[PDB]
Image (cartoon, rainbow, N blue to C red; front, side, top):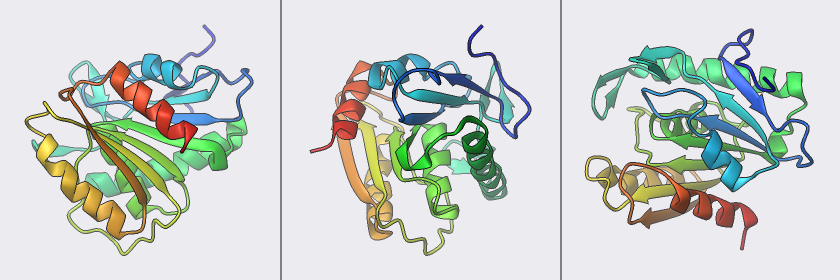
Length: 209
């Protein structure tokens, strides 16, 4: 097995493509209730030769995992977001040192709960994220510090058919914009599920104007 689950850092993770030619890296953060293997097929479609850090959430949820505790749908334990985001920030640095990851060439790609870890990371621990791709995200932090996100490019992909979570996307665009992020937000015909249309857009966004 070329990419076993590595468990001696703060978060379990698999490291894929580390011997391939690209200097680019993607940190992958899965949706709730699943594991770190789930975004690997999408990631490969996006960047087949990138080093992938496929990280696992620390909170069990059924047969999978999640990134921070939920109180009820749309409402999350704020102490949990803070703790897990702090832990993940430390982990990024550990993982980067260990594997020679260039964080000036790294994208943080999250789905749903994982996207909401990434956006929280940007707001709570500045200086780590430069590029973020947020698939079906929503605002999760009740109190946001006055963090300056100037220079960060963020892609958001909302689903038109995402009945439950679609309505919260404008608020996230406003929030990240106000803090100085360069936001590129899309609505696609998809629901809450992600797939090839998402990969096509992330690729297009990475390739730049």
